[PDB]
Structure formats: C-alpha cells, structure tokens
Amino acid sequence: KRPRTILTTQQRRAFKASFEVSSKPCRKVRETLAAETGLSVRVVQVWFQNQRAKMKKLAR
DNA sequence: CAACACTTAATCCAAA
DNA sequence: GTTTGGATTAAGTGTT
C-alpha cells in the first residue's frame, strides 16, 4: 500500500468548490485541480468518487 | 467489433 | 470504543 492522504483546508476548499459545479468533472479539470492543490490526479478522482456516494445515501 | 476510459456499490482499513 | 473518509477491489457502463 501507499500512505493515505490528509488535506489542507485551502485544498479541501478547492475540491468542495469544484464539486459544487460539477459532481463529475472531466479530466482536463481534474488535471487543473491536481496542479492547484499539488496532489495527484488519482486522489482527485477518488475524492470525487467518495463525496458522490456520501450524497446519494443522504437523499435516501 | 479493438482498446481503453470512466462509474457505481460495496468493502477494506487506519486515522481521528 | 465510535465516527469520518481515503484507498482498494470487482462489478458494471461509456468513449473513441
């Protein structure tokens, strides 16, 4: 395994913000989010994946 | 169709 | 001695 991630507020601010606009960001966006936050692209993809399921279950 | 790309639902697993 | 979410795995779908 690889070590798991922890986020700056400024970084989470960034992710939470972009999710406000598309729940399903395309790759060229994910790419920008990586550069912005200094993170890997995969992390971006899974954070969106995880916050998506979080919401589908609340609306049950 | 070949050849990859991406989602979804469920789960593992460690940090909080 | 519970709650939160990040990462992983095995099902799907979608794009080109």
Image: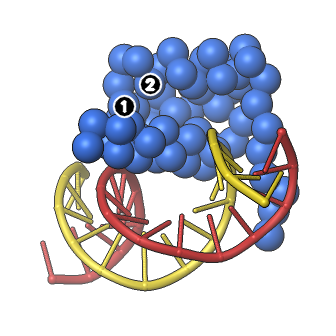
Chain colours: A blue, B red, C yellow
Whether residue A45 is visible to the viewer of this picture, yes or no, is no
The correct choice, above or below, for A38 with respect to C10 in the image is above
- Neighbourhood count class around disc 2 (C-alpha, 10 Å): few under 14, some 14–19, many 20 upward: some
Residue A15, percent across and down? 57, 24
User: In this figure, which residue is indicated by the disc labeled 2?
Assistant: A19
User: Which residue carries the number 1 mark?
Assistant: A23
Q: Secondary structure at mark 2?
A: helix
Query: Do marks 1 and 2 share a subunit?
Result: yes
Type of residue at label 1? Ser
Left or right for A55, reference A5: left
Q: CB under 8 Å between callouts 1 and 2?
A: yes
x%, y% of residue C3? Answer: 63, 43
The quadrant in which the C terminus of chain A is found is top left
Q: Chain of mark 2?
A: A
For the residue pair C13 and A26, the one nearer the viewer reads as C13
Q: Residue at x 28, y 37 (%)?
A: A59
